[PDB]
Each structure stands twice: as C-alpha cells, then as structure tokens.
Amino acid sequence: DSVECPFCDEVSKYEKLAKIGQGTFGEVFKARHRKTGQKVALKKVLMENEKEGFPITALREIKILQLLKHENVVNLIEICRTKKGSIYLVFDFCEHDLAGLLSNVLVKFTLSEIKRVMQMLLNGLYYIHRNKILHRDMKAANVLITRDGVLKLADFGLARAFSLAKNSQPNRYTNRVVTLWYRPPELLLGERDYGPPIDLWGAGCIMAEMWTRSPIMQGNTEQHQLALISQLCGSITPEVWPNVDNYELYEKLELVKGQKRKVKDRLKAYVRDPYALDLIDKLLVLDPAQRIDSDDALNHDFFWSDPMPSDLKGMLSTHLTSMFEY
Amino acid sequence: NNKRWYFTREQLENSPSRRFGVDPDKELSYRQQAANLLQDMGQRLNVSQLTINTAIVYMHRFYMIQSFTRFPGNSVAPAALFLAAKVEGQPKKLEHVIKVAHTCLHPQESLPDTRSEAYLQQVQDLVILESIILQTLGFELTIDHPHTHVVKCTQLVRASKDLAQTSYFMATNSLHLTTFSLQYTPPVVACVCIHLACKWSNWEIPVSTDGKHWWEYVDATVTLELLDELTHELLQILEKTPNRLKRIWNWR
Image 1 (cartoon, each protein chain N blue to C red):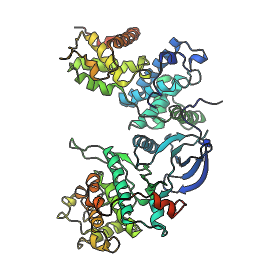
Image 2 (image 1 turned 90 degrees about the vertical axis):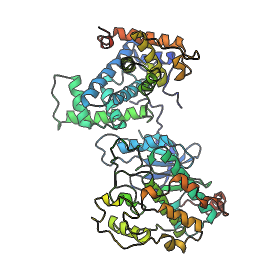
Image 3 (image 1 turned 180 degrees about the vertical axis):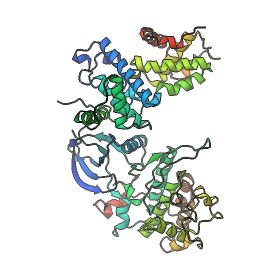
Image 4 (image 1 turned 60 degrees about the horizontal axis):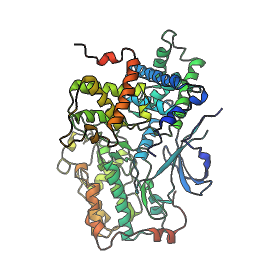
C-alpha cells in the first residue's frame, strides 16, 4: 500500500523540459508547473553508489540552501520525491548564467551594467559569509541571472560551514575544492585553514572575465596553474606574503622565483576604467589576509564613479529572448 | 511555516495512531519506549545526547504523521538515530548501527550472517525507512532544543551548579517522557524545566528589581499559571518513572 506524505510532493507535478547544466553531482533539467506554468530548475540528487543511505553531502547542501534566503542567492522552493526512489531539489528558474553570456558574442556589457553585476555578486558573498558559509566553487557557470536582471549565486554542492578558529586549534577543511582556474593560491599550496578570501579570489577571476570574456588563467594541472598565477601576480615570497614559507610545498614544488607583479598592465588592454583595474587588483592579491573583503570591495570607488551601476532588464529582453547555457 | 510541527491538545488527541485503535495512554508509552531505545542505542554508538535528542524529536514529529500500527517504534528508532547522527556531524556506519540495534532488541540472539539474504534485507529495510522519515518530515531536519536556552536560562538566574545540572535532567527527561516538544517552543520548555528544578531544590528565584519575574526575560508568552500546569504534568510522569527521580534526590 501507500504511505501518508503531506510535506513532500511528487515531482510529477512538474513537467520536465530540457537538460540545462551538466555539472558534477548535478543533473539539471528545466521544468514547468503543470498548473501554473511556473518555471523551475530540478536538481536530481545523484545516488551513484551511496552505500550509506541518503548522501550526507546532500544533506549538507540541503541544510545550507534552507538557511540562505536572500535576493542574490538562488532559491530553494521545496524538495520532491518520485514514488528505487528519487529525490529532487526544486529551485526558482533563472534564465541566464554568466558563462552563457560571456561566451556569446551577441552580448555586450556597458561599464555601468558590469558594475551592477559585480555589485550584486559581491553583495551575495557578503551575505553568505556573514552567515558563516563558504561557497567553495566560484566560477561564471555558477552565477545566474534572471529575466529581470537579478544576479544569483548558485550550486552550493561544494559549500560548507566555517568556524572561528581559536583555542589553539587551526581548522582542517578540505583542501581540493573550487575549480582549477578559479582556485586561489592558499589552496594550491595545500592550506586547510582557509576562509572567506577563497571566494573573493574567485570573484576576482570573474571581474576580469567580464571584459576578457574568457577565464583569465587556464591551467592543465595544479603546477601549471600556480605558475600561471605567479606569472600575473608576481613571485610568492615571505616579502610579499609573510610566513608563506611554512607550507610544505613552498619551494618543495619548484616554484618560479623570478616574477614581478604584472596584473594591471596585462589587463589594461581589455578593461579601460582605472577604477575597475584597481579593484581587480586588490581582489587578486596573493596573501589571503591582504586580499580585499566583501564589505570593503563594495565601498570601493568603482561602485561610486560617474558611470553609476545600472539596471539590466532592458538589455536582457532587447538583447535575446533565449536562455544562455552551454 | 514555523507552526507546522507544533500542535494543539485536541490535535495530539486525534493522532494518526488514535485512528487505528491506539489509546492515548498506549501511544504515549510507545513514544517513551522508542525514546529509551534511542537513548540506549546512542550511548552504545557513542553519540552525543544532542544527537539522541534530535533523533527523539524526529521520532515525535514522525508519529504525528504516521501511526504506530503501521510503523513499530522498534524499526523507526534505529533509522531515526542513523539519520540524526549524519545530520549532527557524527555519522555512524550503516552496519554499525544495525549491529547495535540488533543487540539491544535481542540481547540473546546472535547477529545473522552479514552475507545472508536475511541480513541484507534488514539493511535495505533501514535505508527505506530513513527515506520515509525524511519524506514524512518534509526534509526539515534542523532541530532546536531546550538545552540551548537552558544553559543560557540558568546563567540568567545565576544558578548553582547543582541547580543547573538538575535543570538539564528535567530538560532531557522532558524530551523522553512527554510531548512538550510537540506543543511548546524550546525557550518555553526550558522555563518549565528551571521552574520545576527550583521547586524541587527548594530554590526561590528573586523577583526583578522591577517586579518582573525571571521568565519574562526568556519568552514573553510565559505565565506563571502555565508553568505551574506544565511542571505538574512533568513531575507527575516523573514520579511514575522508576528510579528516575532517584537521580536528583537529596540524600544527605
């Protein structure tokens, strides 16, 4: 027979449409409420092996999405079952993502619009950080925008909660997180007591990506990355980055010794505005404790200069009526 | 919203189990029994009381939707616990929780062949049940407990260590023995725990310099009249519980 279930609707009440994102631990359809036409995104809980009942990392994600209710963070509407069995995460549908826009050449951003995007992106980071959450997966692909031009951070699959590390016991978080290209130096050198700044780095890589239309530092492996970074920010030394020696991989990874900071310069050609440059710079700072934070970044003169942040709705509609996603 | 898992006295009366032949009295004991099973298991599996409480809350809420006649306490508990453990950052391995559950319910029998079909089925059985639990709870697994406020609520009346201890005991037994957690917010239950703890320890909480009673600093909705009714129900069932009261009795 059947079991009572008042608080978990069958996913049948949504009509699948098209596979929109093929990320890791994410099989993302689009869907339509069979009654209201309301569009949603369905993330089916992978259960590849999971020989330990419901996937804990899934429980983690679920706890987090429920806690984050904010305008620049994706929205979990509910959770649905199938009646083996399957579990679906249901979110408010958003029509574009930053990856789909930056690649499509039919799309162009004015300086002011770009300002709004970053303003929205940094504000969202301020929120989650204020809620002691790390996103740990910063990349254009995980940044969505609705029809009405609202930016929303998404995919908290890798996200985890963080604590104030005192009592003489540094944290042991997982080290191999966030995509390679958008990954920060602290993690490559094998840090396990990292914090908010790791997402800020990601945010840096995105800023540039707004003008360059392409992930600025593409690396084959963790070694090719670290070099590629140093070839933009300069050489990793105790002079520029105090106590960077303590890492077991410091030069025990054959790091390139001769490099001077060539960030502003290598970018001037793409981004013209001197303010934008100055920000991208304080975001792509090597030493995490010297890298700019969500709060201060917002207060940067960039967000307060003649070309003031604009709303995006007009562009999105006039631009294309289609949704940009791989 | 935030009232879904809180019920009225009439609602508790007309439970899912009532509608299948179960007397109020019968049912309340099924709960206590499940709680006991949990407490026992959790100790053996070496999880925090916090975890065991979360389990107990899951169990309570669960049987406000499902009936004991369809789901026997003995099968739901291990699943509830298993879930609570993962949820609270103390995961226990599935086999590990089945073993312990077995020995508690059948202290004599020996564990089946971990290769047999019998065993494999009770493994699938628990995973299924944990699923049903998740669904019945609408995947709302973040729980808040009186103990959080009772550490802060005792600090608020500058209580003795003994009076504090005693308070926690009330707190935890309230969870096992009564359905308070299905009726009153954690803050409130904490007050009920402390009030009774005073009455038991012949401790008198001094009225504020204003005239306000200590509980108004915790949950405005709390009236002495209520506290007196709850502490009465709580003490009543405690007295019926063997050896329980003995643990806080002043013997000197």
